[PDB]
Image (cartoon, rainbow, N blue to C red; front, side, top):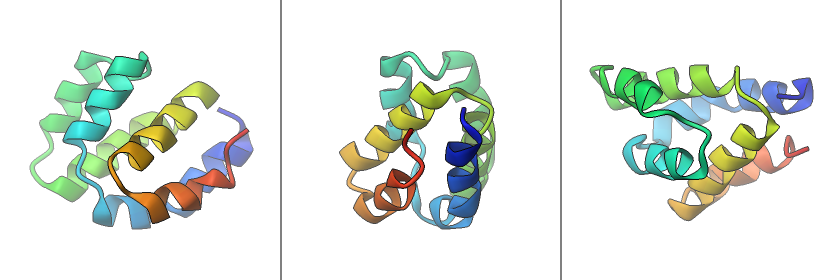
Length: 92
């Protein structure tokens, strides 16, 4: 993704990992076509909620602009309003 978007995600990574549940967010991204079942399974293999969130974000940082926007939308749809707001800045 564009460095601006990547940097925005890196900036708010800690906040995201501390709050988000990955299960439903990933369902949305898979539905959108920006996360594979292979990736979902790897995320799921992480022991804790935060470790799963860390792994998911680690994968997203290497994806494209559309993936960033998909992540943003997933956050909104799951009610993480403030967290999505933090990333709004990086939307290309």
